[PDB]
Amino acid sequence: VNSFSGYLKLTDNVYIKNADIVEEAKKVKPTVVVNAANVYLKHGGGVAGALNKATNNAMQVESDDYIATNGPLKVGGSCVLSGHNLAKHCLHVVGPNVNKGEDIQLLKSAYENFNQHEVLLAPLLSAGIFGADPIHSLRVCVDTVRTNVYLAVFDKNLYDKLVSSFL
Ligand SMILES: COC(=O)C[C@H]1CN(c2ncnc3[nH]c4cc(F)ccc4c23)CCO1
Image (tube, rainbow, N blue to C red; front, side, top):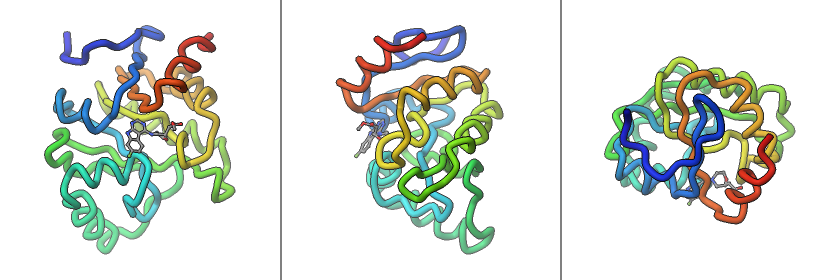
C-alpha cells in the first residue's frame, strides 16, 4: 500500500491521474519524482521549469554543479539528484525532444531508467514542449516500465484523451 490517491489503474503497474506534478509531489513526498530534463539540466520551462521553481531554484543550483563536474547527460539517459522539498530524490530523465530533431526510438531508452526505482511519480516523457505524441509516450511507458509508476498529466483534456484511447 502507498499514499498515491485518485489514480486510474491502466495496467498491473501503471497508474494515471489528471494532476499538477508539483502539487502531487508536494502532497505525497514520493521517494522519487521524475523530471523531464534536458542534457544540460537547464530547467527553464515545461515540467522542469515548474519543478525547479517549486524548489526556489535549488534544483538548478544543484544541477549546475552536477554538469560542471560530469558534463551533459545523454539523450535517453538520467541522473539521480536531490528531490529538495518535493521528494526524497529527483530522477532527471532526458527524453528525445522532437523540436530538436532527436530520434523518438530513444523514448524507450529514456523510460528504461524508471526500472531502477520501485515506485515513481512521473510525467509522460517527451510530451508537452518536447513535442512527442503523448498517446505514444503512454504506450511506450506501459510497454517499457515494469516498476510502479504514477503518471501525472497536467492537462485535463489530454488526460481524458489518454484514458479514452488506451488499449
Ligand atoms: C499540455 O499538456 C501536455 O501535453 C503535457 C505538458 C505538461 N507537462 C506536465 N505534466 C505534468 N504535470 C505538469 N505540471 C506542469 C507545470 C508547468 F508549469 C508546465 C508543465 C507541467 C506538467 C508534461 C509535458 O508537457
